[PDB]
Amino acid sequence: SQVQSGILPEHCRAAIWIEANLKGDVNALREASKIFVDNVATFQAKFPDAKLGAVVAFGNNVWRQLSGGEGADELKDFPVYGKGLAPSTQYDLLIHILSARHEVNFSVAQAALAAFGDAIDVKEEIHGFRWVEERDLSGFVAGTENPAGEETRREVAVIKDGVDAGGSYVFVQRWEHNLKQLNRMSVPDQEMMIGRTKDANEEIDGDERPVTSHLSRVDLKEDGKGLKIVAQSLPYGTASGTHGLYFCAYCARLYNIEQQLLSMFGDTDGKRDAMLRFTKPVTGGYYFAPSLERIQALG
Amino acid sequence: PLGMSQVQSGILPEHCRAAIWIEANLKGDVNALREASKIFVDNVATFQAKFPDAKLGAVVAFGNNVWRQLSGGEGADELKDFPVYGKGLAPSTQYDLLIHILSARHEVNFSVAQAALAAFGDAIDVKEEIHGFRWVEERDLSGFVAGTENPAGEETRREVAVIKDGVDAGGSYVFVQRWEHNLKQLNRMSVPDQEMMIGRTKDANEEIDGDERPVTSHLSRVDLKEDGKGLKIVAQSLPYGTASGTHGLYFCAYCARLYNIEQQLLSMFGDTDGKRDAMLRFTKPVTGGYYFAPSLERIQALG
Ligand code: HEM
Ligand code: HEM
Ligand SMILES: [Mg+2]
Ligand SMILES: [Mg+2]
């Protein structure tokens, strides 16, 4: 089973995420998905330098229909976390496009919209960009502990066997940063909020940083085994309007993502991520990304 | 370089892949713009030093009312608020301040835009912020190549865009106008009909002779000569928007005289000969403003 092309690429410069609801017959998604994955292959051949990839992924209700109820055992609608502190905006379809070249991504996004046509209702379209020094707009480097290299990224993100082999679970969550609130914090206070130093990007020892620090919330182990995810997140927005991080992660099980969210939003131990001092999530959804062979076998 | 006037760095660069434009109104006393503009151009120099490979430039430019105040009424003789053209076919949304940032790196442009906002602070009310991107093959989102006849090279671009002498030497006039394309409407037109609308062939970008295209074609509207002398402008326009939402062309041009821009607008919008640009069949302008970009030396004499 071959993995969709947008899960594994590293260090992308730009992305487009489109989140949409199904308005028409669920069966219209079958032909549209095949059209789109062929478009992606054609664009990769036309723009080899772009290192383009893309993913089509499906919400719980749609995917149960498309799959006949087989597999994707962990899939569910995204719930609130923290009783609502993390909101839920579960849609039916996610299209994630990434590459070195925003302009290529834009053409690919137009192709996705042509493939799905008026069967879908676009609810969100976000254009991500890698910022200076791969920093989040807060000024902290983002991506350091992300699984590195195809071998490890496959291990973390790609389902190994059975009916879902080559697929992955996806989580997307848009955050809105209040950089004015951030900038009122001293740099040492910001560093204790994240759990790494700001300029030099060195981890602060877990025994010496707050348990509410981001790293303490999300660097989770189960009897010594890390709960890893493959992030594809990027900055987005305008300088004068809304801006933040579009969080996007892939994992061979939803479990690892969910444990991190239960931790961040106070459900596990009553403590909340210190980043909520300056940024907040405003969307959230879970999706299942089938393998390419599974997509071809739809219609 | 005493006794000379240095152009702001964003007027002349060619083939930059990314831009940010910010348009804003002044909220309080115009004096706030003096120290903010000096800070901003200094920040630009710092970003150029930090990111030499970005090939970054930027411009700060001013609307008529605030430029008249800051200049004491000296110079900028052609400057005026952007008029409506075609009785409203081209709307007017004249603001007080234009920031234009362009480079080979969107991420550097973003940092520079943040610096501009920090410099001006609450003295301004941002009315729009547009992130331009060069599309594939330098095409407009309509699919036609954009930029072919734009003045080429530093020498010619300086001749067209940069005022040569007098108090305004090193300055330029700026026009910005955001267009919203209806690509569904465009795609209802056959490609031959689109070519007659533009005046060039779509795939190969060959000019269609003036006698073989309608007078409403875009090239017939805007390729204007006065007794054989072309009325040139230096465009810095780029595509913008989302695939599923608003998208189009953010039109931006610089010229040493506002006259050349105005003649093209009077032509496009029906004021000269009663005919209008065929591109209005699929796209429309929704903003419009004129600004004056002083020389970099003069931004330093503010205060
Ligand atoms: C505003 C939103 C977020 C910001 C700004 C942010 C920022 C960061 C930063 C600066 C780091 C440290 C550098 C690195 O290793 O990448 C980090 C690490 C990490 N983040 Fe986040 N993050 C956000 C949301 C999330 C969410 C929602 C999750 C999971 C559901 C998450 C999971 C992780 C993980 C697993 C790590 C690596 C921890 C480690 O093993 O050291 N992050 N994040
Ligand atoms: C929807 C907005 C616009 C679109 C899509 C558009 C597109 C084009 C295209 C495809 C060309 C031919 C290729 C080239 O030489 O660049 C062109 C040329 C040109 N455009 Fe536009 N344009 C727009 C607005 C404007 C405006 C508002 C003006 C002036 C006020 C203008 C002035 C020019 C000029 C002077 C030329 C060169 C003509 C020549 O000498 O051959 N354009 N434009
Ligand atoms: Mg660790
Ligand atoms: Mg000509």
Image: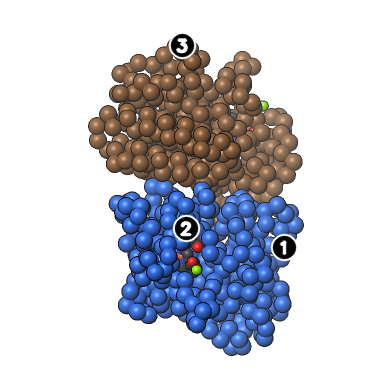
Chain colours: A blue, B brown
Residue A125 to residue B137: above or below: below
Mark 3 vs mark 1, CA separation in Å: 58 Å
Q: Which residue is mark 2?
A: A202
- Classed neighbour count for the residue bearing mark 3: other residues with Cα under 10 Å, few (<14), some (14–19), many (≥20): few
* Amino acid marked by disc 2: Glu
Instruction: Report the chain holding disc 1.
Output: A
Residue A238 to residue A253: above or below: above
Task: Using the image as rendered, state which of residue B281 and residue A77 is in the foreground.
Answer: A77
Mark 2 vs mark 1, CA separation in Å: 39 Å
Q: Mark 2 and mark 3, same subunit?
A: no
Secondary structure found at label 1: helix
* Amino acid marked by disc 1: Ala
Q: Which residue is mark 1?
A: A41
Q: Does the CB distance between marks 3 and 1 fall below 8 Å?
A: no
Q: Which residue is mark 3?
A: B3
Instruction: Report the chain holding disc 3.
Output: B
